[PDB]
Image 1 (cartoon, one colour):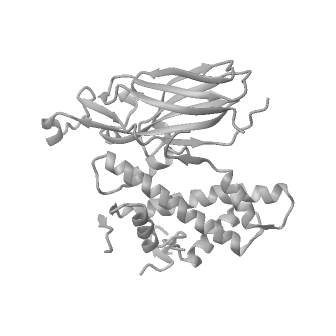
Image 2 (tube, rainbow over the protein chains, first blue to last red):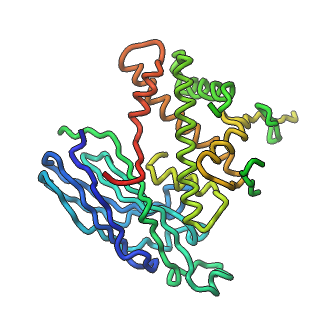
Image 3 (spheres, rainbow over the protein chains, first blue to last red):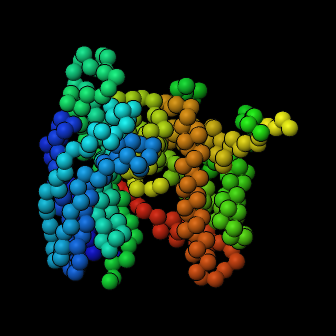
Length: 155
Length: 19
Length: 75
Length: 85
């Protein structure tokens, strides 16, 4: 049995400008208590083709974890556009929420993110160099992908 | 290019150059 | 069973030969690998359809497959 | 001294199979590159599961791999769900 279950993730303040932070409201349940920390991450996929352009937006340590229900606001700053390939900048990518216990990730909640110009002039002819100040970031929060992994919980 | 999928012979191996 | 058996069995046996396992596969085992491969790939294509729709695209691209893959945390 | 190099273009799944699986997933249109993408990812999948299975048959000593071994190894993969719980 898994000692931690993620009951809900709420995507807050979306759509938002690209440079706005990610705010997730994470509610999880602890069945039996944990001595050491859970580790939550917000991973951002900056290029679909490679993990090299993965950006870790924030990482938080939560522990010790008593049994019962928890809710907290995980917030991370927007990704660094200098690390995003320009060909992957305007379009779809994914953002991820991750939890880790004893070094092994037991849950990954993904979301499809669409970065887009709202300006009709920029929709017509986008700049050669992507303009992130005019980019709206739309997370698709109605289709989260929740992936559970098998993990050693003992000690 | 794009392939329209709505109901629209490939041997096992092939050979090209580069030696 | 939508995947033709001969090329699939060939590929599976080649993969086994890279791992140098030298252990014969049960015919029903390779069949199970085929069925699971079909289910896997179909679910993948559902995810790619969703990804392309969110990208304002009818045509699905290799990027959609890669994103559908990383959203599940595989290699 | 002039050589043409061998290449496997089926890579375990044919084109009509790929297109059919894409239609069963609701995809109405694809780029041709999808083919070489699918043939790639399929390999990875098998490459994982085979390993997951063989070590199974390696830890419990056997000379052959049962379909039960690959069902076990398949459950040793991750389970992605469309919602929470």
